[PDB]
Picture 1 (tube, rainbow over the protein chains, first blue to last red):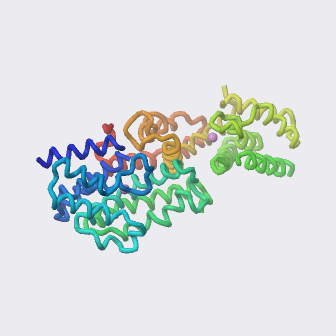
Picture 2: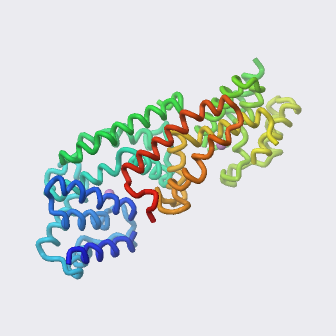
Length: 193
Length: 188
Ligand code: NI
Ligand code: NI
């Protein structure tokens, strides 16, 4: 029954969307949730739908909290599960959540937040940061909105904001690679700093 | 030196026209470096390096210049007609090739590989609505179709030696992505 529901939710979210990012985060959250003894169905479902309500979305695609909730109930998902998924997605998406350092999140929420931050670092994070700059018309370097300045202002600090022990061990290799990339960039572009 | 003043004059004009500049500035410095090693005419190398994008179809119509427009400005700035002709001949061929043009092309290709080349490919993908991976238009495909071939297309020995270390770092980056995104190669 749970393999059917997860498939229904995966289809529904794919048709709406970006998908590649969310699919990747869903898979990484289930891996961490396994090592962290989290409820795995909760972890996967919330990872698949947490972006659906995000404010950084146009009004044409952005669903409300009630709309997502009712869709889960219509898919057949139980009351305890629905509520817990809603708790995760609301606690991740209020303004300046970062002030509370993922402390109000349950173990399931923590795991979903960690996968999200892991997707923003290493080789994949480097890629996403530069795509974003290209999409928003920002520069490579030499500027406070540039992708280069985003490394020092945000991306290199993320390793110290992980919630779970497994996420912290997974971050070490990714963070190390960013430094090697920055190093290579600094000799590819003499005077970048 | 008259060469120094003339080059400064060109730099200020190009930077003024493009309001990207940062890319063209790197490529000019790298071209001068390669040219010095290869015994090419450095003034021609630097000047061709600075103006060749101005006529490239990439640039928007609100900024892009014709060949004669580039020619007229060079002559107005005091560059001789013999030098102006050589530069024009280089930048039209690029858009076979002389020693000076081979050096400039090599510098262009080098800015497309290594760390800076990884950055530039992903920026372009975001700009045109392309994905990270998944189809023939994505940044990942662009590595395998184009950017990893560039080291076989270097004209000079100097550039080739410089390409070695950049190409290898790029291969380490692909390796890192394959590790962090299991199944990246077959993903739709
Ligand atoms: Ni996200
Ligand atoms: Ni160029």
